[PDB]
Image (cartoon, rainbow, N blue to C red; front, top):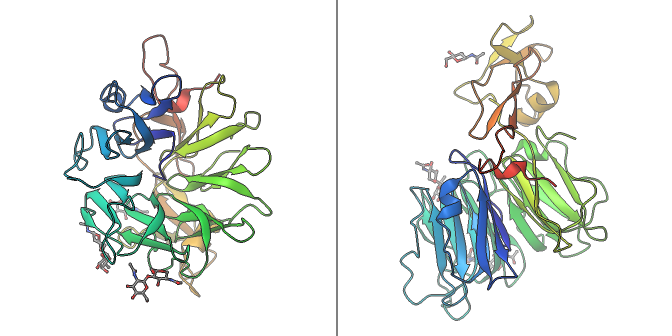
Length: 369
Ligand SMILES: *[C@@H]1O[C@H](CO)[C@@H](O[C@@H]2O[C@H](CO)[C@@H](O)[C@H](O)[C@H]2NC(C)=O)[C@H](O)[C@H]1NC(C)=O
Ligand SMILES: *[C@@H]1O[C@H](CO[C@@H]2O[C@@H](C)[C@@H](O)[C@@H](O)[C@@H]2O)[C@@H](O)[C@H](O)[C@H]1NC(C)=O
Ligand SMILES: *[C@@H]1O[C@H](CO)[C@@H](O)[C@H](O)[C@H]1NC(C)=O
């Protein structure tokens, strides 16, 4: 998820691993976490200028050749350097199951593709116009035009709406993509604007917040304040960020966020930013009932019901009725059930940091001072 930076995180079923460019070394990457493939597969002496991560893989932009070099255990992302030839790339961005690479000016041809992408349902060349930056969602990638600074997205739009609902006309300084939404900092005034049919935008942007950079998970978004350089995170199923430590940059996994401290002496910190819950779909609509929800199901809160309800329509015929959704069975890799499924909420998951002894190699989301 997100864009290229000095730090990156892999996430998903294979574990959670934080990779960072060591400035004390020759811009060589060093990783740690539960995604063992993304730790020990890292190139041991390949100088890199940037990093980006996805579901079980991390890709770096080489210094020498300025081409993508990927490692990890994602079946849709090839290990090593993809079939590029002579092209060179300005930036990288990794989604769940795909990598996108913004071509350098020297490798760009007029009226031709600006981005090369590899991955599931994403392998090909895209936007036929120069872009400044690129960012990747779960199943899509976005970018800002060099001409008018307006955003454009490509890929699978299902569940997000980020391609058609893109604010073509607003000019952005930078944009970051979450799992099903995109947030950006406006060029004029540096306000934060987001789009995409996601519960990460259920409450909206924190009032009066000016950020320098943004990162986003599946259903959450974090930002660094302009002055204090302190993190401010919001979104779905988010618990009440480290308030003390200022950061120079952030990076977001699917359900955790890591930050490179502004002070180079202090080590990296990571914290959980939520957990997945079963939500009603077209195929699994959920039971509208006037009575409390039966065992094994929970009453979806009225706030999210209104958010998931179409324009000018109620989700259940009788608005007072409870919408009962099946309780989630289990937690994703690295997390364990912290709270049981009640009649009012789904089961809550937290990252299992109990097996973090010496030479245990636990999740990257468990690293605090
Ligand atoms: C911003 O600039 C881009 C690139 O110059 C524009 O994208 C092109 O717009 C023309 C005119 O509609 C289309 O014929 C092309 O197919 C577009 N190219 C691509 C790759 O999509 C974009 O329309 C401009 N937007 C604004 C608001 O100025
Ligand atoms: C692969 O991604 C597709 C996205 O395609 C885009 O949206 C559709 C509606 C068309 O306008 C197409 O030209 C666009 O490129 C998804 O529609 C499709 O379901 C995805 N397939 C799988 C197997 O995930
Ligand atoms: C729970 O799942 C079963 C089987 O997948 C389905 O038939 C049922 O409708 C679901 N219950 C609710 C309340 O959605």
